[PDB]
C-alpha cells in the first residue's frame, strides 16, 4: 500500500551523463554509443543570444573547440552535426555503460523522470509531467541544460526530453532527443511565454482511482454524468477536456474498482465545486495531475 | 527555479540490489563486498511469523537453502549470520559495483531516498522522511522487503534504512543496516500500530525558505516570535518543538533570504492559526515537511553526486 510520486531508478541514465564545454559555456551531454547529444545553444556567444544562426555558428566550429569530459576522462570529438536544436558530437569512444535505449516524443499529460545534472554530474532525480502548455515544472538551475527526461521500459530507457531553457514564470522548456521543441518555443533569448496552464484531467481521474484502490473513498458520490456535461464544468475550472480516448484508457482502473469513468467524473465535478473541506486524498490537499493511468496501474501492481 | 521532491541518483544502490529466496519467500538483498544483507523474516513462512524464534530458525537453515541471484547470475552463499533483525549472507563473490559506503542510523525528521525493488530489481526511487513516530510513508507492495533507504554525500552512499513491514494504516516500518528497528516495532505478525504522527517543524521552515528563494512571499509578515511562544503554539497543532539546534541549522537559509528564523516562525504560526486562505506555497495547499534544511540548500544551489 501507499502512493508516492516515484521516479524511475536513474542508474542507466547516470552512466551516460557527460560534461560538454564550448568556449565559456559548460552544460550536460548524453553519451550514447559514440555520440554525445546536447543542446545546440552550447555554441552560442554573447552576441548570438537574441537571433542566433546556429547553422552559421556550427560551420565555424572545429571538433577541437568542443571539450567533452566523462568523469575524469576527456573524450575526443571526431565529428559534429546538428539535428534541429540538438548538437551531436561524434566521439572516438563508445560509452561502455550505454543501456538499451530509444528516443521517444511524448504527448502532454505524459510523465517522466528527470535526472538533473550540473557539469556532467547527476545531482538529483525527480518526476515530471509534460504540461498541456508543453512546459515542464522542473527544478533546474543555471548549468542544468542538457539534463534529460526518461522512462524505463523493463530494461530499456526511453529518452523523451532534454532541458534547454527556463521561461520567465519559472517553468521549463526543452526538446525531444531529435532536437524538436515541445511547444511553441525557440532556443533564442527572444520574448517567450508559456500559454495558461491547465490541469491534466485524465491524470486527476487516474489518481482518484489510485486513492480508491488505497482505501480513500470519501469523495465518491452516487452521481454519474455525460462526457459533454463533465467537459463543460471541468473547462470552467481550467481542466483539460476529457476525450473518449481518455475514458477508454481509464477502463482497466474502472474495472478494478467497480466505479464507471463517468461515475468518477461526477466525483471530480463535486470536488471542483466543494473543495476538500479540510480533507486530503492520498495525503494531498490539492488534486494531483502528474500520475498517468499507466503510472497508477504500475505502482498499484 | 522550481522546487521538486528530489531523490538522490540511485545508480550506486541499483548495482547492489539482488534477489534473496528462502523456501517460498522472495525479497530483496543489498550486496556489498562479499555480504548480502536482507530482513531476517525471509527465513519465515506461515507459523514462523506468528511467534518466531529467529535464532532457532536460522540454526536449522543451511547455506544452500538461501538462493541469491544478482541479475542473471546465481551467487553461492558460503556463510550466514544474524545481526538484530538483519540477516547477513556471506557470498563467494565480492560485488564489483560496491560503492564507497557506510551504515548510518538517522533521526526523525531526516530525509532519505528509497530505491523500491521487487525480486532484486529496482523499480522506482522516491524521497521520504523518517516520521517523528518512526514510520515512513512509503510506497511498498509485497516483495518490496529488503528495499533500502540512503543518502549520498560526495561519492559516499550512507545506507540508513531497510524495509521490513507495513502497518495497518498503510505506513511502513524498518531497520537501520545493523538490523535495529526505527520505532517500537517488532518483526512478528502481531497487533502493532504507529503512534500519532507529528509535523517536522524545522523541515516546514526549510520549505518556507525554499518557497521564498523561488519567489513565493505572500506568507511573510513583519512579525517575529520567541522560541518559547512559537513552541507553545506549535505543540497545540501537533508540530514538533523547535530547538536551538534547528534554529542554527536554518541559519544559512536565514542569511540567504534575509528572513530570520524566528521571523519565519511568526509566518508559520499565522499559517497554523489562520490557514492558507485558498492560497498555495510551491504549488502545495499543505505545509510540506519532508525537505530538511540541507535538502533545500542542496537543491537551491545544485550540489552533484
Ligand atoms: C543552460 C541554462 C540556460 O541556458 N537557461 C536558460 O533558460 C537560458 C537563459 C537565457 O535565455 C535563454 C534563451 C534560450 C535558451 Cl534555449 C536558454 C536560455 C536555463 C535553463 N534552466 C534553468 C535556468 C535557471 C537559471 C538561469 C538559466 C536557466
Ligand atoms: C516483504 C513483505 C512483508 O513481509 N510485509 C509485511 O508487512 C509482513 C506481513 C505480515 O505481517 C508482518 C509482520 C512483521 C513483519 Cl516484519 C512483516 C510482515 C510487507 C511489507 N511491505 C509492504 C507490504 C504490502 C503488502 C503485504 C505485505 C507487505
Image (cartoon, coloured by chain):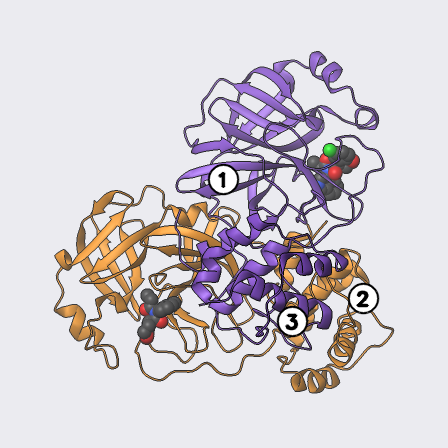
Chain colours: A orange, B purple
| Quadrant containing the N terminus of chain B in the rendered view | bottom left
- In front of the other: A117 or A262: A117
- The residue wearing badge 2 is A259
Q: Position of residue B91 (x, y in %)?
A: 52, 19
Estimate the spatial distance between the alpha carbons at disc 3 and disc 2, rounded to whole Å.
15 Å
- Under circle 3, the secondary element is helix
Chain to which mark 3 belongs: A
Q: Position of residue B114 (x, y in %)?
A: 57, 45
Estimate the spatial distance between the alpha carbons at disc 3 and disc 1, rounded to whole Å.
32 Å
Q: Are marks 1 and 2 in contact (CB under 8 Å)?
A: no
- Position of residue B119 in the picture relative to residue A279 (left or right): left
Residue at image x 46%, y 67%? B258
- The residue wearing badge 3 is A202
Q: Is residue A101 visible?
A: yes
Q: Position of residue A110 (x, y in %)?
A: 54, 66
Queried on whether the Cβ of the residue with tag 3 lies below 8 angstroms from ligand 2, the answer reads no
Q: Position of residue A109 (x, y in %)?
A: 56, 70
- The residue wearing badge 1 is B14
Residue at image x 51%, y 51%? B249
- Under circle 2, the secondary element is loop
Question: For the residues tagged 1 and 2, is the chain the same?
Answer: no
Chain to which mark 1 belongs: B
Eye-nearest disc, 1 or 2:
1
- In front of the other: A235 or A47: A47
Q: Is residue B142 visible?
A: no
- Give the mark nearest the N terminus, 3 or 2: 3
- Under circle 1, the secondary element is helix
Amino acid at each position: 500500500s501507499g502512493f508516492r510520486k516515484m521516479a524511475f531508478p536513474s542508474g542507466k541514465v547516470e552512466g551516460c551523463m557527460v560534461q560538454v564545454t564550448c568556449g565559456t559555456t559548460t552544460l550536460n551531454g548524453l553519451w550514447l554509443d559514440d555520440v554525445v547529444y546536447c543542446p545546440r545553444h552550447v555554441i552560442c556567444t554573447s552576441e548570438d543570444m537574441l537571433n542566433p544562426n546556429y547553422e552559421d555558428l556550427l560551420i565555424r566550429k572545429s571538433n577541437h573547440n568542443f571539450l567533452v569530459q566523462a568523469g575524469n576522462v576527456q573524450l575526443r570529438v571526431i565529428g559534429h552535426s546538428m539535428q534541429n536544436c540538438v548538437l551531436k558530437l561524434k566521439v572516438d569512444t563508445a560509452n561502455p555503460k550505454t543501456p538499451k535505449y530509444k528516443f521517444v516524443r511524448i504527448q502532454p499529460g505524459q510523465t517522466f523522470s528527470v535526472l538533473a545534472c550540473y557539469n556532467g554530474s547527476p545531482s538529483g532525480v525527480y518526476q515530471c509531467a509534460m504540461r498541456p502548455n508543453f512546459t515542464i515544472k522542473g527544478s533546474f538551475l543555471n548549468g542544468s541544460c542538457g539534463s534529460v527526461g526518461f522512462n524505463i521500459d523493463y530494461d530499456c530507457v526511453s529518452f523523451c526530453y532534454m532541458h534547454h531553457m527556463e521561461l520567465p514564470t519559472g517553468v521549463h522548456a526543452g526538446t525531444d532527443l531529435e532536437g524538436n521543441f515541445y511547444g511553441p518555443f525557440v532556443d533564442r533569448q527572444t520574448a517567450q511565454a508559456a500559454g495558461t496552464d491547465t490541469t491534466i484531467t485524465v491524470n486527476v481521474l487516474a489518481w482518484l482511482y489510485a486513492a480508491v484502490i488505497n482505501g480513500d473513498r470519501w469523495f465518491l458520490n452516487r452521481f454519474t454524468t455525460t462526457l459533454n456535461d463533465f467537459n463543460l464544468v471541468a473547462m470552467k475550472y481550467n481542466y483539460e477536456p476529457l476525450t473518449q480516448d481518455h475514458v477508454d484508457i481509464l477502463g482497466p482502473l474502472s474495472a478494478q474498482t467497480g466505479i464507471a469513468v463517468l461515475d468518477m467524473c461526477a466525483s471530480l465535478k463535486e470536488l471542483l465545486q466543494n473543495g476538500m473541506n479540510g480533507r486530503t486524498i492520498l495525503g494531498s490537499a490539492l488534486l494531483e495531475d502528474e500520475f498517468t493511468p499507466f503510472d497508477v496501474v504500475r505502482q498499484c501492481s
